[PDB]
Structures are given as structure tokens and as C-alpha cells.
Amino acid sequence: MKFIVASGELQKALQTVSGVISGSQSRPILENFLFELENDNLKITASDGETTLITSIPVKSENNGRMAVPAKMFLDVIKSFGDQPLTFVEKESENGIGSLLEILDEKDNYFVALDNAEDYPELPEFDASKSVKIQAGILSEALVNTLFATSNDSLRPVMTGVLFQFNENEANFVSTDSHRLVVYNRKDVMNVDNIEFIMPKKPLAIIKNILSNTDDEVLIEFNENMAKFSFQDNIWICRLIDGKYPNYTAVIPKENPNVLTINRNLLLSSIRRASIFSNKSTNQVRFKLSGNLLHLHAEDTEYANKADMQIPCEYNGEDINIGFSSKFLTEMLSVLGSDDITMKMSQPNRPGIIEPVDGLEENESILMLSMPVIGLAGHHH
Amino acid sequence: MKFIVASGELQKALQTVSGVISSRPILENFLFELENDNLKITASDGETTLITSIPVKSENNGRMAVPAKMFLDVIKSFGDQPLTFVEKSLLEILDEKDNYFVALDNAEDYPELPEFDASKSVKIQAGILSEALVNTLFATSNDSLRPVMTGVLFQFNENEANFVSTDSHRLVVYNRKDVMNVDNIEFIMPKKPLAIIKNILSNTDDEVLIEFNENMAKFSFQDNIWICRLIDGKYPNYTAVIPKENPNVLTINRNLLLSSIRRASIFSNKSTNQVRFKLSGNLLHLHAEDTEYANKADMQIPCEYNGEDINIGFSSKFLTEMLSVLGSDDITMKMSQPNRPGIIEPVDGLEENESILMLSMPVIGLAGHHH
Amino acid sequence: MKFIVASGELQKALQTVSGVISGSQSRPILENFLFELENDNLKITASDGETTLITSIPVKSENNGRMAVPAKMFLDVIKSFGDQPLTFVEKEGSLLEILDEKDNYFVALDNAEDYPELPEFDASKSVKIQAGILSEALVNTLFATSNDSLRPVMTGVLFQFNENEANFVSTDSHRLVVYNRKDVMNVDNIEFIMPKKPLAIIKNILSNTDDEVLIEFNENMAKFSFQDNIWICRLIDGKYPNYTAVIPKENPNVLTINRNLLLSSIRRASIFSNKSTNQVRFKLSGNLLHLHAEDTEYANKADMQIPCEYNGEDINIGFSSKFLTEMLSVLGSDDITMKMSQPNRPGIIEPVDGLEENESILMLSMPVIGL
Amino acid sequence: MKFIVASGELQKALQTVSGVISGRPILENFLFELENDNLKITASDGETTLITSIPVKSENNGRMAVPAKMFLDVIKSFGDQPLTFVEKESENGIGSLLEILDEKDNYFVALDNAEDYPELPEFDASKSVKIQAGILSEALVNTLFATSNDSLRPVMTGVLFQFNENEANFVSTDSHRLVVYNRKDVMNVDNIEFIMPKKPLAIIKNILSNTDDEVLIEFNENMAKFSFQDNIWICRLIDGKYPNYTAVIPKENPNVLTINRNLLLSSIRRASIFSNKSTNQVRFKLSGNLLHLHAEDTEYANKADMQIPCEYNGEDINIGFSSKFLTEMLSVLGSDDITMKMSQPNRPGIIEPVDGLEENESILMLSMPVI
Ligand SMILES: [Ca+2]
Ligand SMILES: [Ca+2]
Ligand SMILES: [Ca+2]
Ligand SMILES: [Ca+2]
Ligand SMILES: [Ca+2]
Ligand SMILES: [Ca+2]
Ligand SMILES: [Ca+2]
Ligand SMILES: [Ca+2]
Ligand SMILES: [Ca+2]
Ligand SMILES: [Cl-]
Ligand SMILES: [Cl-]
Ligand code: NA
Ligand code: NA
């Protein structure tokens, strides 16, 4: 097969599908891009066996073909060029058992050895039974809010992923670990098909880098156990996590009369400083709230360091003494971008509910629950 | 004052009370009070006061403030020898033809304790109290708990004594139906004096008297006195967090479970140190993994399990620490759902009126918390 | 001691000297910053036992003192602030208190008396050099130093000063850089070998200014002084290799070529190169450079034709692409010459443009040799 | 690669070389090289390289970089059982995994890139000496405590090795203590003198057995290569001139104290508690057959005065020594009695064991006096 394509267009297409190639040589055929050339359309596929990324670009050609091109090398090769048309010709090695990909650029020649394309598996016929639509910019903000930066909990399978709930009234995006619950809600995302599914983290991270922040629609189609995203000339296919996500709404305390209103960056930077003085193993801080004063306390009995900070705030509520793991709390505060947050509390053994004060669009809301540190004897019952 | 005492006896007395000396400078001293051949030795950090006394040979009485680290270092540097001490303000030590001097503080500056006016009292055998502390004093606890949960709850009434401790991962309830006192009392002991008391208490039938006033406990045991400031507040209602129905019973060799978790946890993330249990049939599957570094462990442990399949996760350090305190060959762990505590109890070795209950809180995503 | 200073000023000073605290110091006292306060001047010292970094900043205070502050933690603490005045109070198990309005922080301190003092430096010789010239010397030489602790002299940079010029040489036996400045003239003639690690640290602290750096010498130490910084380093003992014997007197085969063009061409060609030697072949004839790379293990190949100016006989010579690209990326000229003799002799790269009047650079690459 | 080995042998092999891995990231790995049922294990900190080898069962060859702390922790968690190790490609990343199979249990340890682990350097031996393992080990037992722990004056941080055709000398000093260990039964044609650094010697002391098995030491410019059974140790030698240690040792020392070692040691330990906190000095006042020990701390008002009967033939002398250095030196000796030979109150005292030395073995431990 032979085709001519602008190197910039080729690089962008290759870069889009490359995030799923892990460098693993356990299935060596999956270290390749799969090129499929048909009627001036170059379809490029990469996969790790569970996530598959596909894109296509127009090219100039007169013939068809299929090629398995080693991905890391070939992308490095394309990256080494400026913007110029490149010619690609598959040649059978004059001495060998397989075939070469030759690149022609003026008087210069390059050869990249190819794998056996017949060994690159075909994807199965996707038989969509349901589909939803969501704008790319909305989906990417959902991923900004639900994908945690740290995740060192060994959770059960349904909670290791992100829940997507779509119905005719709204969409919900939910994630959790032992310290946090994020519920992100869009009442402006409405679909006839009611569907619920759990997306694993790795394809979500891969998709997050590919998604643009635009009003362009993403189609998501579903079969037995896969989701198929379609966005411009891209297709992303992911294995879903089987099972039923817990009834997360039942965990949200109904009454939270103790409302802290505070500048977000002040609370975030204060906790970060205080936790430097706590025990390196647990990184906990205590909140003592009373009047319009937040008293932060951290100490490390092993090393004799201590922090005591008084932070002015708006607090209408009863005196409360409540402890938190600072790393998980500050990560959530870093995800919000508002000037002010509220943290609504009830008892020291119940989660605090963090919400932005400002900065939400009309039909957008987010709820961030932070589970406090509580001795087991004082658990809710 | 002047007295003669064998260095070994003096050393044991000093070591008994030295554990509380860490504070303001007068509290860095031992307080010596000599009265009719009885040398009372007092040490304090301002909240806990430890007292012991030993017989000595003397002809007069007195009071001295002796700097503790220095003096115990000195006594330790001797072999077993009768030593003469003369207060002169210096303390002179005489050993045959050898002379030593230690500078002294002003004893008049050492705070006296107020006269203790007991309103209630309980008694408990030292061995019973000592076992209670073995079961409730955690080897490590790094949680910043609220003040009432940083201590150990003592409950005495006419029917039983209860000893309860907790952190974010554990609840220990130690019950003795053979410890009965007329006085009903409930109080929270801070951990630090409890640790010192655990090392001094013997495993004997000698009785420990505990007396109380407004907010102090005074323990008496042989020639020791321990006076501790109690933690103010009410301990939480711990019985309400113990699940009532636990149809899923694991019976398993404790040492095998303990060593298996220890190995598997080497393969977990160093930050959280968690293992997942997959129970089905008579087989426990242990799984640990470190997603950051691609390490993994999968182990199969034979057991007796009659119950439904369960997939439940635990923090290994806190689980293994409680299992290490128990001494029976087998334990039962009773579970219900993956978001509820598992109840660990020994199979053998409890006396007639002794029971131990250990709750392990599992690792559970907040979305699936109990409700 | 007690002093007040803006957090931003303290952070920059700490950051200046922190690069020599490498973490796991075999002596734990060397994990501290040493603070010495004298007449409103806070002198801050860090050391790994061989290199000592010193800076000082003005502060507001009423007394003097000495403190050893744990470095990693204290820098973390200062970094966690914005630009605000901070109050520091030494409380001598010695503590450091930090006061900010109504907020209080305590950092446990080590014993400053345990921090080693530096010996009185007894300078016998000294040279001066502009900071910008010295840093340019380091930019050109540090990448070529060896990383084997086998030949210590090659892990450093040779410094040569006399009344006519300053010369800087580095090598790892595969590359040689000679950097020469005839506008750096000092009465004292001195020759010495500086270790790479303090040189890298110094390179980041040095600014690109005409302000002078003083270097003073005693038996086997160099003391650099530059503004309010002092850097004291142990010199490498021994004789630097006879590097001029590696430069052939004649290199008649001269390639003249655009630097970025040669650099980007080698970069592309190297993707196809031998994973073991990462070799690119230059085939020169007429006014055409042919670049060839191939990977015998994986069946990839590159053949590139670059028009150039070449005066010499036909030559086919191989070089390590990693070393060649590193060297071409350090130079900044539009054009370079590469002078060669035989296929088993070095290629010598020099910039054509962009050098100051009394500045010259020589970058030698050993060829690839194989059967 | 795939191999089977007893867990106990693997643990012993790993612990032998693991002492050199401190906290470059590639050097935190063991390097495994498997060839014809021989598993060679390498560890290094970049300056010291330790190598051991053990027989294993295998059918293929290979190379692995195994993370050391984790892997040794893993091996330690097993008892004595055969373990199977299989290198597999990672399923989700670019690296490679080491699988450990124990019956139905599977464990995976992520591996580093072995191609990034440095090869051993070509050793070009020019000279060699031989010495029994036990003799060398005893030499290090006597000398390592005396080395300086200040990195100022590097050569004093090592132990001098002197071999010639007549004897071997091992010398250490920190300018306050000097130890000379002499063996007139260690003879080699090659006369060699070199300085070994302290850290590898401490490791080497523990690997060496107390047997007549020969240690071969080969040398080049600044590397020593020790070979002892299936171990290889490669260390960078310390360059520079060791002090002329023979000039501080007085030849004539007419004032000789002979005394039980434990009696002098325990007596100095006691006195040193009462001594000057800055110098920790004790005075010897020797006359007749009486040793008067005196210590005092004028700042804190403590004093010690001891009379010890002894054998002293000499003139009345009043001489002070550091009790900390004296007690350490007496604790390293193991004889029943020691002699301390003195001359003037401002000249060193020389301590030697009285009994227990072999015919051609001598020990000299010199203490610089306080003045
Ligand atoms: Ca066409
Ligand atoms: Ca509906
Ligand atoms: Ca928004
Ligand atoms: Ca009497
Ligand atoms: Ca019992
Ligand atoms: Ca001033
Ligand atoms: Ca700042
Ligand atoms: Ca000259
Ligand atoms: Ca073992
Ligand atoms: Cl979970
Ligand atoms: Cl709590
Ligand atoms: Na008195
Ligand atoms: Na000070």
C-alpha cells in the first residue's frame, strides 16, 4: 500500500490514539498502530486489549491495505519532521520474511520494519442497544471533578470506577474512595435512553486528554459490556465494569445545620501548611469551629512538631471538633475553582458536604463529601 | 538526711517511677521523702504522679529533690553494693573510700500533691488489670482522635468490669464478669500512664485498689501509688456500633492468617497498606496490590467458612496488630456485609468469666457506607 | 535568639544553599540548615561534609544566636507561606517557634553544638572571574564530565588560570571540551580540579552578570565568593589526564554545516540507530553529507542526504548520536565546523559564529570503533 | 529467565551483599545474573560493589534488576522452602515483572531495567597480597572504632593497610586515638600500602569468617578487589598521604599501670558521668599501687573521686584522658588485664592487652592526653 499525507495531520492523528499503547510487550502485536487504508481514508487503531482508540484522516492514495506499524518508534519518527508531505510505501523486504514501511522525503529514505498485520485482531461488530449524547465540554468537566489525583485505596470493583447515570431529566457522574464522594449533576444533559454504567479509570484518563472543551456532541453507545464513544472522527471503545454501583445518595446526611463559609484558597493553603506538622503516616488535621473562627490543629507526637492556626470565616453553627485526612480534603478543594466554598456539617462522625459558592453554570451542581476521621466507638449508628 | 541502701534495690525503685519523667524544670527531679526507714520516691510530669517506696537503713528523716536522669545513670553505673547517701545543696554518695557529689534542686519547690479525698473505690486483681491492658493498649495508633477516644474506658459496677479502646480502625471490648465492686464508676484513663502501669503490674492475684475523687484516679498496688488525671467527657456508646447479626463466620488459624497478611501487605501500596479478603467455601483468598508500582500478591488460605461469598477489604497494620494481641490458636471473625465491622474473638483460652471482642472496620468506599 | 524576616527573602536564601543537602546524609546532623544570627545578619549554612554552601540575608532582630533547623521540613514550612513577615523564636530537646499574627508553629530542633564548624580558611592564592564567564564555562564543560567513580579526576572540571587566560577542560574519555578565555587574567597562576556535583550546584546559583567571583585557595579547598554567597569545596587530588595528546595536530577533512540542520538530522537518524551504540555514520564526499543509521536487531534504517560545505577526502566515520546531539545542542552558533582526520580518530566541533572576542570552544568526539 | 532456589540460601546470599545499598535510583536494585545454574548477585552504591554467587536450578540464562528492600523483605517472609522465580513481561507497562510461585500462591515484583545497571569495570591488577580471613577480620575489629567520623581530612576516615615481605600493619586514627594492629605472620612478595574507606570495611568485617581461608586483594591505581570464597568486593581506595603515625608513638614509657580491664572500664564509665560535659575528662593520679580517678563538672557541680588498687611501678603522675575515648578503647579489647604505659603528663598513654594474643600478633592503642 502507498499513500501521501501531511506530516502534521499524521502526527496529530497518531498522537490521539497513542495514549492507549502502554509499552507492554506481553501482547507484542498490540504495540503497533493498525493502519487501514480504504478509498483515501486512513483509519488508525491502537489498543491495549481493553480500551481501543480509533481515528481516521484523509490521505492521497490509489490502493488499499492493512499495516501493523510499531507505535512508539513510528510516532517518534513522525515527530522528528516539520510540516511536509510524506510518502509511505509498504515494500516486501528484499531479504526477509516480512515487509517494510518505507518513508520517502526528497532524496532521503527511511525504512521501518512492520509486524504481521494478519495478527492484529479485528474488533467485534458493535451492536448498540442504547445511546446517549453529551457535549464534549460537559463530559470533560465531569472527568475533571470525578477523577481523583491520589487513589491508593483497594476498593471493591464497582467503586474503583466512575458511575455515569443518564436519563430524560439529568446526568450524574459519581466517584468515591474511602474518604470522598463526588456527585456531579447536569440537569441540562437529557436523553431518552435511561442508562447507568461504570467506566474504569484508565480509559477515562486517556479520554480526558483527547476530549476538547467544546459544544461538539459525544455519542456514547452501549452493548452488553462495552461503551463506544464517538466524537468527530474518533471512536473510543472501553470495557465497562460489571455490577451495580452502591446507592450513594443514601450516604449523604440529610440535615447539615453547621455551615462553614470560607475562602477556598485560604482554607486550602491553611490545611496544606498545617498538615506539614502532622504525623507523616496519617496526615490528619483537627477543625475546631466556634463563632466565626476556625481553629486548625496539627501535631506529630513522634517528632514533636505542632501547628495551631486561627482562620477567620463565616460559621453559623454549634461548636464542633472534627478531624480529617488532609490530603484527600485538599485534593477536593483543589478540584473546585470558586472563590468561596461552604462545608456543611452535622456531627463529628458524619461527612462534611463541600460545595462551591460561585462559579456553577445554570444547570450544574457538584457535591463533595469528605468523610471525617472518627474513632470506631463513635461511628454513626 | 542520711541513709544506706543496696544499689540494686535503689535502682529498681528508681526505674519503677522513672517512666513519667520527660516539662518545667522542677519536675525533672525525683522527690525523695525519708520517714522512719522508709524512702518514698516520687516522679511526676504534672498530670501523672508515680510513687514507690523501699526500706532503707537510716537514723533521721528528710526531703530531697534529685535530678532524675543524672541520678539513675549514676546508680546504674554501680554494681550491687551498699551505698550511703548524705544530704549536704549537694547529695554525697559514699562507697568505701570513694566519694561522689550530685548537685540538688530545692525540694521546697517540688509541688506537693493535694490530700486525696476518695469518694469511691474499686478493687481488681493485678493479673486481671494487666490482661485488660494487654488487650486494649494498641502497639501503634497514629489517628488524631477526639480527647475521649484517645484513652481507655474503664467501667466498674456490681456485675462486671469493661475495658474499651478504639481508633478509626478498631474497637476492643474486654469484659470480666468476675470483677465486681459495690461502687459503680466509669472513667477514661489516658494512654501514657496506662503504658507505664502495664510494665509495673505483675501477673499475680495481688489486688490493685483504684480510688477516685472529682477527676483523678489513684491506683495502689504493693508499695506503688499511681495518680492520674482522667479524661473529661463521656465515652461514646460503643455497644451501638457492634453489629447484632453476623451470619458469616470465618474460623481460621490465627498465626497462619497473621503471617499471610504480613507477606501480602509487602505487595500493597506503602501509603494505605490494604488487603482484600475473598471468602467462599472453605478458602480465603488474600489479594494485595500496589497500582502505583505494579506489585501484586495472591494467596489461598485454608479455613472453615460457612456463610455467603464476601469481598471485604482491611488495613493490614491495624488488623494484624489486634490479631497479635490474642493468644488462641484459632480465631473466629464474624462478618455481615463488606461495609460493616468484622468481629474477631478467640476460639480457646478465655477463663470462665472473661470475654474479648475485637471489631475491625473494613476499608469501604464512602459511596457504599452503611445506612 | 529571635528574629523577623519576610518569608520570601528567607525562602530564596534557604533554596540557595539547600542543593547540597542531598537527603540521605550519612551524618544526620548534616540534614540541618545552620542558622547563625549576628548583628541583624542571618548566615545560613548547608553542607554534605565535603561541600559547604553559605548565604546570608539581613533580618530584624535584637539578639544573636545559633540554631540547627531540619532542612527538608523547614523549607517545606517556609514554602507553604505567601509573602509575609515571619517571627522566629529559639526556645532551648530545643524547639523553634514560628509566629504569624495569631498563628503559632513549633519545629523540633537538633543540637546546634553538634553541627561541625568550618575551619578557618587560610587563603594563600586567589583569582577573579566574572560570574557570567564562569557560568558559561560550566554550561560548556559539565555535560562532558565522567560519571564513573572509577576515575575521580574525570568526574571534575579542570580550571587553569594565569595572567593570560583561563582554561576549562572536561572529558569522560569519549568527549572532550576545552573552553578558553583570554579575557580572564589573574596574577596568581593556579590549576585545580573541581568536582562535578558542587559545580552543578554552583552553576544554578551563579547569575549571568559581569559581577566578579572571587576564588580563594588553601591546601586542597576552593572558596568561591559571589555577592552574599560562599561555596567551599574539596578539590580533586591527582593529575588531570594529558588531554592534548588526544587532539591530532592535523584534521584536514573539514565539514562546515548549519548547526540546527546537523542537530535535527542526527536526531532523526538516531531513532533508527543501533540500540547498543546509537551510532550514525557520516559519509562525506564532495559537498554532500550522507547520514546513515541502522538497527541490525530490529530491521530499521535511515539514509539522509544533506548539502553542505566539505573540503577533504572521502571519509566514512561513525559517532555516538547521543553524545553528538548533546554537544551540538550545547553550542548556540548558526554554523559549526567538524574537522576530521581518519575514521578511527576524533571529530572536532567548533562554532563558527557567536563567540566573544577572547572566547574559544573546542568539542572533541571519539569515533565509534567496531569490527 | 526461570530458576528454583532454596529460600534460605537466597536470603543468605542477598543479606551478604545488601549492606551497601543506601537510600542514583538504579543502584537500589540487586543485579541478578543467571548462567549455567549459577546465580550471581551484585549490589553497589557506586563506589563499593559487593558480589556473591549461589548455585540454583535452572535451564536458561538471564539478567534482572530487582528492587532490594522490597525483595529482601519478600524473601524474609518465607521459611525454608524451595521457591520458583519466573521473569515475565508486564501486562500493563513498559517494564518487566518477577513472578514468585509458591504452590497455588503467586507474587509479582516489578523490576527495573537491567540494561541500565552499570557493568563491572575491567580490573587491571598490577599487584596482589593474601591474608587469612580471620586475621583481616580481627584487624578491622581493632581499628574501625578509631577512624575519624568527620569528613574533614578524608584519609583519616579510612584504615591504612601496609603489606611488605615481613609483616602486615593496620592503622587507624582520628588524631585523638591511634590503633596499630601488627601481624608478623602475614608476608607477601608485593610490598603495598593503601587506605581502605570505613563504610565497606564495616560491611566486609561481618562477611568474613574467622577461618584461615585466604582473602586475595588485587590493586590498580585506586581500586582494591577482594576475593574470598564466592564473594567479590571492589572498593575505591582513598588517595593521599597517611600521617607519619610512627612519630607520635613514644618509644620509652617507663610508668606502667597494670589493671583488670573490666575494673578500669566500669570505673571510668562511672566517673565519666561526673565529668566535664565539654571534654568528658577523667584524671589518673598514679602513685604507689593506687589509681585515683577524678572527674568533675564545675558548671553543674558534680564530682567523682575513686580509689582503685592496682599494680603501678613508676613515678607519681597526674594525667588526664577523654573518658569516652578511653572507655570505647577498653571496650574493644577483650583481655583480662591491660597495661597502660605512660611517660609524661603531656605524652600519650599506650594501652595493650596483657593476655590472649597469638605469637606474631600485637595490638597498640594510643590515647592523646588532655592538657
Ligand atoms: Ca485517490
Ligand atoms: Ca425515566
Ligand atoms: Ca462549570
Ligand atoms: Ca532507723
Ligand atoms: Ca487470660
Ligand atoms: Ca538590630
Ligand atoms: Ca513564597
Ligand atoms: Ca605565568
Ligand atoms: Ca527464612
Ligand atoms: Cl470498597
Ligand atoms: Cl475521634
Ligand atoms: Na531536705
Ligand atoms: Na542556640
Image: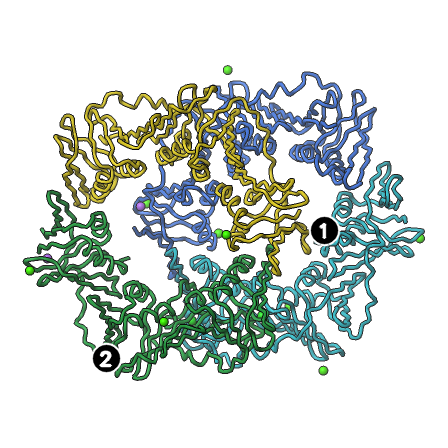
Chain colours: A cyan, B green, C blue, D yellow
> Is A297 above or below relative to D18?
below
Q: Residue at x 70, y 65 (%)?
A: A137
Tell me, yes or no, whether the two marked residues, 2 and 1, touch with CB atoms within 8 Å.
no
Q: Secondary structure at mark 1?
A: loop
User: Amino acid under label 1?
Assistant: Gln
- What x and y, as percent, mark residue D163? 43, 23
Q: Residue at x 22, y 52 (%)?
A: B72
Q: Residues within 10 Å of mark 2 (few under 14, many from 20)?
A: some
> Is C276 above or below relative to D7?
above
The answer to which quarter of the image holds residue D339 is top left
Which disc, if any, is residue C355?
none
Specify whether B243 is left or right of C360: left
User: Amino acid under label 2?
Assistant: Lys
Q: Is mark 2 within 8 Å of ligand 5?
A: no
Viewport quadrant of the C terminus of chain B: bottom right
- What x and y, as percent, mark residue D219? 51, 26
Q: Residue at x 21, y 34 (%)?
A: D259
Q: Is mark 1 within 8 Å of ligand 10?
A: no
Tell me which chain the residue with mark 1 is part of: A
Which residue is tagged 1? A25
Viewport quadrant of the N terminus of chain B: bottom left
Q: How many marks?
A: 2
Distance (Cα) linking label 2 and label 1: 74 Å
- Between residues B159 and C81, which one lies in front from this camera angle? B159
Which residue is tagged 2? B120
Tell me which chain the residue with mark 2 is part of: B
Q: Is residue B157 visible?
A: yes
Q: Secondary structure at mark 2?
A: strand
Say yes or no: labels 2 and 1 on the same chain.
no
